[PDB]
Image (spheres, rainbow, N blue to C red):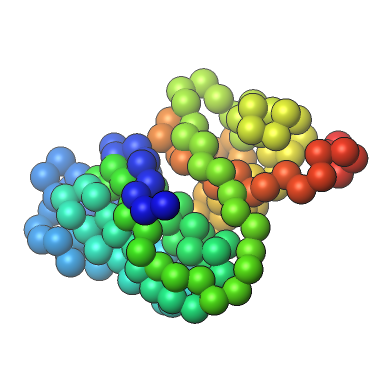
Length: 157
Ligand SMILES: [K+]
């Protein structure tokens, strides 16, 4: 209900994660820019803070999908180990799970893990977008956003 845990070393290499580059809001700056570069929706609706590697998102008035959306992009920074969600939602949306890619897994393999079916790799990857590069282009530490598999009966191919 507050903090989310991520990988640290894994994610977009925005800065020199070896030390933290320069300063707190500068680290955040990269993150904000990163979300704008990637094209993360509602990334302007929120706000990002950085505490060495503990990022904090805030904002209000978006959907929960938008909120977590930012979390993923912010929590997938090389240098960021976690994201403190402080952003508020104005409209009802479906909540998702967060799965961290392990060394050897593919979008399919993890989809099969989270959904029970690998064919749902797209639902994840496209949801991890535009943060995620490509399905088989994941990387160890990629905490992919796992949308809620509504009605397990049918749907899944
Ligand atoms: K990270």
